[PDB]
Length: 131
Length: 137
Length: 129
Ligand SMILES: O=c1ccn([C@H]2CC(O)[C@@H](COP(=O)(O)OP(=O)(O)OP(=O)(O)O)O2)c(=O)[nH]1
Ligand SMILES: O=c1ccn([C@H]2CC(O)[C@@H](COP(=O)(O)OP(=O)(O)OP(=O)(O)O)O2)c(=O)[nH]1
Ligand SMILES: O=c1ccn([C@H]2CC(O)[C@@H](COP(=O)(O)OP(=O)(O)OP(=O)(O)O)O2)c(=O)[nH]1
Ligand SMILES: [Cr+3]
Ligand SMILES: [Cr+3]
Ligand SMILES: [Cr+3]
Image (cartoon, rainbow over all chains, first blue to last red; front, side):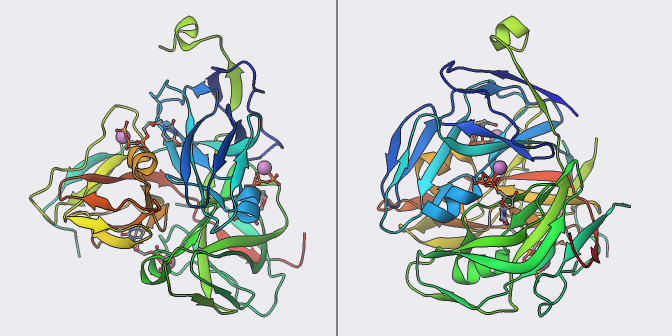
């Protein structure tokens, strides 16, 4: 029941929002219009930056509707947004369809952002495991 | 440690009930209610014959099965599939054959993916003019 | 503060480490050299095995740099490391670029590992919703 500081690098876009209570993420908009040819990819700017709390992590997930209907996916899915990252959030989209192209319009919801805690583990090297 | 329960409805009473192979196993395997064949590069939305009630504050995640991933190149377009807490519909998996030549034959009753459940920070967005001005440089 | 036991099966690679305080994961290296032609995949060794605490889960995430740059992805992303597992972590790399083959050399960072709690939920069958 955390707050996430967000800066709208592109004031021309709506502020990402949680569709329904409980909804895992908030949809991210595309700041640009782009066409992905079958098999081709693209790094798309979302017009936003966020400040994920220390001990937490941002996760860029693909939208299931578009995923099925047009084969639109994310190459590095899940996208990993570190707590210290202050740059702009970009989504590496890819058209996984075999023959049809994917049209992306400035203003479309091209991904969803989730926020979860993360175990900042201290790795301790051992000679072997206990059995 | 001691968690909660997850209410599950077998929409298709012909498939087994998903379960946790081992105690510490992150998730439970989901079965395919249908027979499907994925030609190379082709995809499909396959039904799992189940619906769930992910508790408020938690999310359901649909991950691929490493085995089939390596052996035949089976993947899931929207991995990780996000199952929202308020969703009460049937879980479906967007299976895709990432292999270059060999089709992939899916049989009703096969384990096609696994489902994990985690808590999820239901963050409240707070727009700020800039990180510097907000003291977040 | 949670600690993660880890064995460098291949003593010739650096121990995986967290780039910055706050960074979600730690980059896992490649223990071998591999070239993936377009559309081709390969299960790569990392030269390490870990011991995910009971109640937690490991997760293998692709690195965004290479994904955008050369189209390098992970077939089963996110890779699930169960608490029970004690074998070598292997990554299922795949070349999603149309024409350019991908070259990986021993010592490269091919993936990042995350650890998170997981709800070991108890399934209960019910009649309806
Ligand atoms: O592997 C999946 C992913 C999603 N769903 C369902 C359940 C759920 O929460 C809803 C929507 O998924 P999502 O929010 O990812 O995709 P969307 O394209 O953004 O659609 P929606 O507009 O309904 O939010 O779709 C599944 O059955 N299986
Ligand atoms: O979909 C994404 C993925 C990552 N990032 C940013 C935020 C963040 O945490 C940082 C690095 O992501 P990552 O660790 O995946 O890529 P990398 O290639 O491993 O590089 P690095 O950690 O070296 O900066 O890059 C995005 O804006 N969008
Ligand atoms: O990116 C990955 C994913 C899995 N593994 C290993 C570790 C681990 O837990 C085991 C396989 O568990 P998993 O649920 O992924 O595979 P499965 O296909 O569902 O099969 P099962 O539990 O029968 O093995 O494989 C990796 O090394 N890398
Ligand atoms: Cr939604
Ligand atoms: Cr398993
Ligand atoms: Cr990093």
